Amino acid sequence: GNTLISVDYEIFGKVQGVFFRKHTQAEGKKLGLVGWVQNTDRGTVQGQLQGPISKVRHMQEWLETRGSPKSHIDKANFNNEKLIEELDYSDFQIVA
Image 1 (tube, one colour):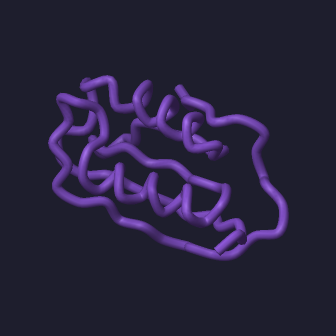
Image 2 (cartoon, rainbow, N blue to C red; image 1 turned 135 degrees about the vertical axis):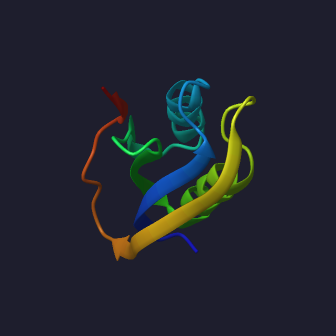
Image 3 (cartoon, rainbow, N blue to C red; image 1 turned 60 degrees about the vertical axis):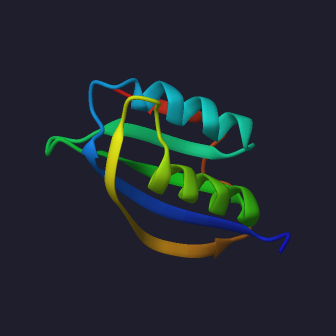
């Protein structure tokens, strides 16, 4: 479609200390997405994605299967997937 969606994500495995945040931001920006990425307090990576639905879906697949080159992804959990009519962000940020 040419609709917009928002979705929350959390990635499990060898996902911290592998340049995951930098690569996620770069891929998000390449895909024209806004949102954020952050290392959690439980050894995972999380955030939200917003943008054109096909681009969000491409990013979801990237988060399931690839991530940063030295990452090892066991699972990507997605939640709160929804259609949106406006963006809630103006950039794709790494949240410290």
